[PDB]
Image (cartoon, rainbow, N blue to C red; front, side, top):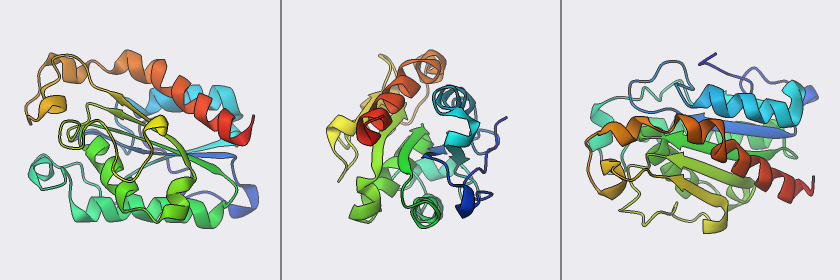
Length: 197
């Protein structure tokens, strides 16, 4: 449920049309955590199990408490891992549309990875959703080097990490409805738009 390695376990002979790469928050289990499974279920509904590959960022991304305090909100190894998956997706399935997402530390991670991402693969990222984006204030609600029309940030009122703090209040753990509704809806919308549908 909370771990999905569709990409790693993915066969180039049987590529999916859409590949979703998601990064969990600090301390979350699996490679998807609490919000990932919700987003995954909706994409599967719109693209069928065979149409989309769900891949969480595991491996070197340990989703450590201390890494939130590093300059970019996460570690260099974590950024390397996610970068590595965008590259694996582009190699195995050059025609698949890419979409991404992250929550809390995973949000800062998604943002750093996309920022460091080679233009070409980045251009393939139809849309990205970020919940409780820890660098929201610092990056002005954007992902550096990634267009605003493709970025959607879910930052609750009262969520202190969205306004420059590294402290958690109730609003930070209240993204469940966003992950079950608005978030996958935005992702499905952008994918359809790029593939035409």
